[PDB]
Amino acid sequence: AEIGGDHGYNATNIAAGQTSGAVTQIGPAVMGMVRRAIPNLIAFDICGVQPM
Amino acid sequence: STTTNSNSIGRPNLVALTRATTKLIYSDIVATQRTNQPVAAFYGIKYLNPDN
Image (cartoon, rainbow over all chains, first blue to last red):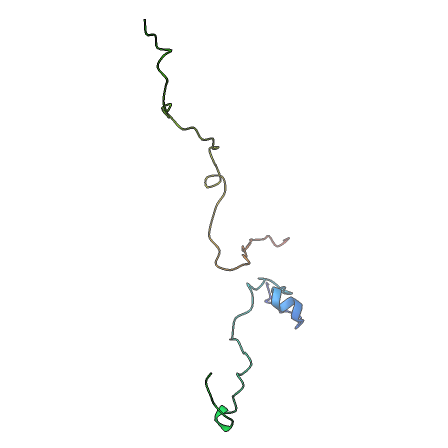
């Protein structure tokens, strides 16, 4: 009676959308993107600051 | 008898250009719809008998 089915929780299939029952998924969603933080800077004024 | 061979012709007149191009037929042969991502997915949805 046309079950939905599911991906085998196998990263290769879920990204492609390969399913087990019916209606292959279009694809995953996009929950967001994460990038590494920008490190901070130790203030230069501790040493000599002489613009040449 | 100053014939026309005494006269010297100047710049010849460029009467007409001529370029060669086929009757390009690709808008009318195939169905086109622009894609917004580097991978395009066309759905195929079918209706089946109880014998598939």
